[PDB]
Length: 6
Length: 9
Length: 227
Length: 229
Image (cartoon, rainbow over all chains, first blue to last red; front, top):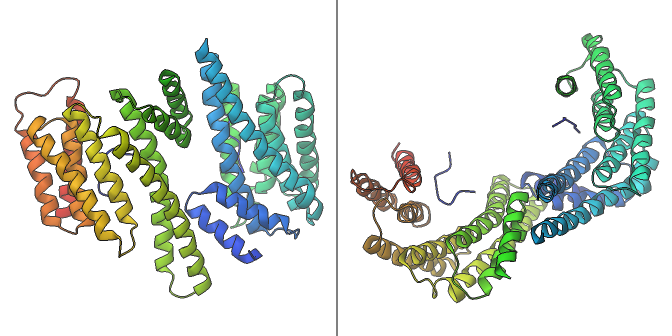
């Protein structure tokens, strides 16, 4: 999907 | 590299 | 145990891909009440991201089956609820560490931004599985944590700093997916990409493999949302 | 209702929640009726994934413990963590082995299914042998060997050389010889005979089973290549 990240 | 057994994971 | 042995058992658990263990070690460390180092807070954050990630992934599978579906429907429903409970218990554990220990002892701008961004993320995870009555309150708590982090990072950090970029990526995901504002999501992501590009002669050895991978993720989201 | 426990097991599978899948299939088995072909494959998939996670962890930690010369507080903590993983792994094997002894093997009413459960007994005793202390090991190794041998004798009497269950048993038995008994000549010889007798079928292999047979035959030959080099 959409990328998020930490 | 690892030799085969079955069932696989 | 003692602080230093707890950290070493966490790294070991990390190598064994035993994430529940890793999170219980780093919870204990945090509960001793001393400010965390860079190395420690990254360990804490990696442990909980893997523990909560496995529940979210399982929730999306079961909740879809329940949709495209009776006693078979009721079963999917019950199984989705048991997964939801495990997920909320995990989020409230993290949220309670943030409020009692981490945010109060944070002595630098950079670490205040890190923890506020984490607080936005974990309220956002609650928002994904909330329904009706509680949802507005939860969505509000996510947006305010994000907004305070965004203001501090604009005032104190360079446009190429990884923590500043990482925040812009996740806050734009919040707009798109939680608030339904594709136009605000796009313009947040585009400004963050362009200001970083304008300043590239100013990235060091340390953060210049992290910064450019997040720039890549920003442009990938835009292309997705623009197609 | 067995039908409902089987539906939950599938659901657990699609969510990648293998401990939940294993608890449902243990309950179905515990009802005392013979398992369908579908139910037997579910049981085997749940437990393969639950025990696999531990074995993979065990190798990571054991290899860190040995590599560390000195640091006797760090080596001690590694040793402790390895032992805790070992205790989880032994429990899982003992649960499986007890289902096989009480319900699955005494009730198996066809050669196909009795070969399948026998091969599973040899596998789970072999997992206990990978982590056995030196006083208990020899007893564990012989249990693995006897279960594989009785399977091997039934399959050679009752099944065609290209049957997937017969081919999978020769693949696992031959790895037992190589790694557990340190007998590479015996391991090679067992793998080569099973490959060659299967090739012998320039004659009869069914269209629904052929893809499985061919895949395992290539696994046998990759092992022979690795062990010859």
